[PDB]
């Protein structure tokens, strides 16, 4: 019986949690919140943490925890399960990537066509989009986005981009809120992750949705793709079943259970989504090194500098 600190979306976690419990009989308690938060918590907690597994939407949350030496090394059968082109890997094998999600511009087909969007995410930080483009200053993927821009364009491009969005864009508390504010026509478009779109259309009916996803591709920073992952805590009193849970996640069955219900890119080579996901290669993602702890820090220094924080 295990306790998962779940930074992942509730739908995501309950799919894999339930699928695991069917295969093993092992119960999963879900403690849901922001990975950001839960990572800080786990730090506070030390050996007192009740958390067996940590499930994150983004690798940086895993990286900091890994930098603190709080994660249990995993076997090279878990790790290798999702070993693949461009997939981030832990120096200490103390976490494993599991699924990928693309950066997207979601736009109102009512008001815009793809033709009318930008060929670079850099360009939304502009008078031209004054109150026309939404962003999420607290989103984990937003942070990885700033990271990418610093690496690909430099930290001057990245603060200028932040400041532009600050001045001309509109902020939202979550990506879902961002997307839903666009569907209410409050906002013409917004920077989000791809998988939210699928979920919306499934709940609402695609015929009732007027937004589309745009794919900047061409190794533009906006074409970035980031990775969700999991890990076992050193403190765990249920280590073996915690390792099993994570094995399940990177294994075929775990990937089919997640990707069956959530529009994220599955990382196990033996698995393919039935969600008509845009072919990852066609994404033309920039080939960006993994986010490092002091790369993540730098970017929040920027977040502060720009007025978001
Ligand atoms: Fe998300």
Image (cartoon, rainbow, N blue to C red):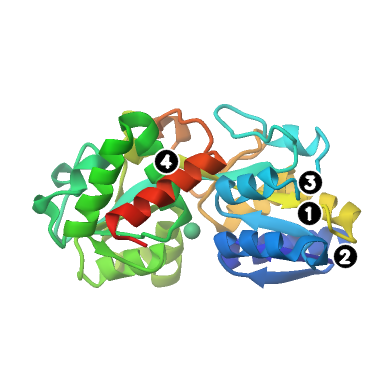
Percent x, y for residue 229? 64, 48
Q: Residue furthest left?
A: 128
Q: Are the residues at dot 3 and dot 4 in contact (C-beta closer than 8 Å)?
A: no
Residue indicated by mark 2:
25
Residue indicated by mark 1:
233
Marks 3 and 1, the one that precedes in the sequence: 1
Marks 2 and 3, the one that precedes in the sequence: 2
Percent x, y for residue 144? 45, 45
Q: Give the residue at x 24% y 72%.
A: 184
Q: Give the residue at x 73% y 48%.
A: 253
Marks 4 and 2, the one that precedes in the sequence: 2
Q: How many marks?
A: 4
Give the CA distance from mark 1 to mark 4.
Answer: 26 Å
Give the CA distance from mark 4 to mark 2.
Answer: 41 Å
Quadrant of the snapshot with the C terminus: bottom left
Marks 1 and 4, the one that precedes in the sequence: 4
Q: Name the front one of labels 4 and 2.
A: 4
């Amino acid at each position: 019986d295990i306790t998962v600190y779940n930074g992942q979306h509730k739908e995501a976690a309950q799919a894999v949690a339930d699928a695991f419990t069917r295969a093993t009989g092992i119960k999963v308690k879900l403690n849901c919140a922001k990975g950001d938060q839960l990572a800080g918590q786990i730090k506070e907690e030390g050996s007192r943490s009740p958390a067996d597994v940590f499930y994150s939407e983004q690798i940086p949350a895993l990286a900091t925890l890994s930098a603190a030496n709080l994660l249990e090394p995993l076997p090279a059968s878990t790790i290798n399960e999702t070993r693949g082109k461009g997939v981030p890997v832990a120096a200490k094998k103390d976490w494993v990537a599991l699924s990928g999600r693309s950066r997207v511009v979601v736009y109102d087909t009512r008001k815009l066509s793809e033709k009318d969007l930008e060929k670079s995410v850099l360009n939304y930080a502009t008078p031209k989009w004054k109150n026309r483009i939404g962003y999420v200053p607290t989103s984990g993927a937003f942070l990885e986005q700033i990271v990418a821009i610093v690496k690909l364009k430099g930290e001057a491009a990245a603060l200028k981009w932040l400041k532009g969005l600050k001045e001309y864009g509109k902020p939202y508390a979550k990506n879902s809120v961002a997307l839903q504010a666009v569907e209410n026509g409050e906002i013409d478009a917004a920077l989000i992750n791809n998988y939210y779109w699928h979920a919306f259309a499934r709940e609402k009916g695609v015929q009732n949705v007027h937004t589309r996803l745009n794919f900047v591709r061409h190794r533009d920073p906006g074409a970035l793709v980031t990775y969700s992952g999991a890990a076992v805590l050193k403190s765990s009193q249920n280590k073996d079943e915690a390792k099993k849970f994570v094995a399940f996640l990177a294994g075929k069955e775990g990937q089919r259970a997640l990707t069956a219900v959530r529009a994220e890119y599955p990382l196990n080579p033996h698995v393919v989504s039935t969600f008509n996901l845009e072919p990852i290669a066609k994404l033309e993602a920039p080939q960006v090194s993994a986010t490092t702890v002091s790369e993540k820090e730098h970017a929040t220094r920027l977040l502060e500098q720009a007025g978001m924080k």
